[PDB]
Image 1 (tube, rainbow, N blue to C red):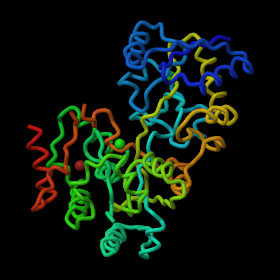
Image 2 (spheres, helix red, strand yellow; image 1 turned 90 degrees about the vertical axis):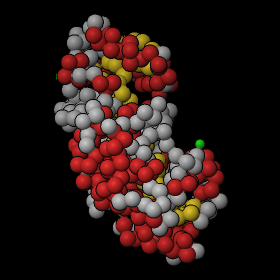
Image 3 (tube, protein in one colour; image 1 turned 90 degrees about the horizontal axis):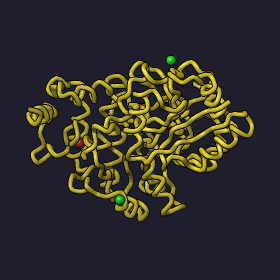
Length: 381
Ligand SMILES: [Br-]
Ligand SMILES: [Cl-]
Ligand SMILES: [Cl-]
């Protein structure tokens, strides 16, 4: 058979090339690839879908699909036999999967800590909010307690994680929605009262430093590898970078206990790439057959000898999981217990974010969470 593919220039890796080469060699599917310059790809894909000339398989950005209507353009893959093998199945707002993902996640947020420092000062892995506060207290008795690094989005990762967890997958999506269409009224967001309270308490006790929050990732790495930071909350990509810089460092990773339900789910970025099937294709069956082969352990294993990042599927031997993420990989990631943090969405980025810079409201004397919500709403109007 034949299959046509549309992909981003910079995403047409040796990984995918060899994947498509195997497909032609072993499965008798002649694949023709059409690459588009990355900054142009969303424009081009939209146009080709609109005029119906789009290739059989197209690269898409998960989870939001460039705001395209998948029920118009893409095959619903939710019932394909390989869906159970996904670690974190991509979903639209109805829970349906419209692409084969190349990774389960871009970024996982966790509390990373220096196991040796914890041992030195008799600190145990915090398994609750009070244990976190106590852990910070002992560090101050003995080194910045809880370090944070700067981002290009609001709210900061720490508050984003906590808000996302209390609201859950639907609630978090709705929050981005109403923030983005400007219908939100922050004084109605009383579900956020306790997590803003927690945030405030960290500032109050000096466990997080407002003046340090603009610290670059490079600075966190520099200080962490010199035993100047006990705990860092943020992206596992930062933890990876710490280990790269100091291979012998003894790093642990656990849930940040900042909400009553923190142990239930991890947050992160699920803004991964995927391959969707063009609904109006005359070769939909062939496309679906191809994705099924691509999803197979043999192909995933070959792919991840080249492709970087976290695996998309269960039992991808060639995908390396960082040792520090080992526990969380088994407890949460492998079980799909991950949802997208509200700061990971494009709308959240300053380019002007749809979310408030809540930390900017925290001055001396500190306001209440009620006052922070009023301030957020005042800036809205
Ligand atoms: Br914030
Ligand atoms: Cl369909
Ligand atoms: Cl940096």
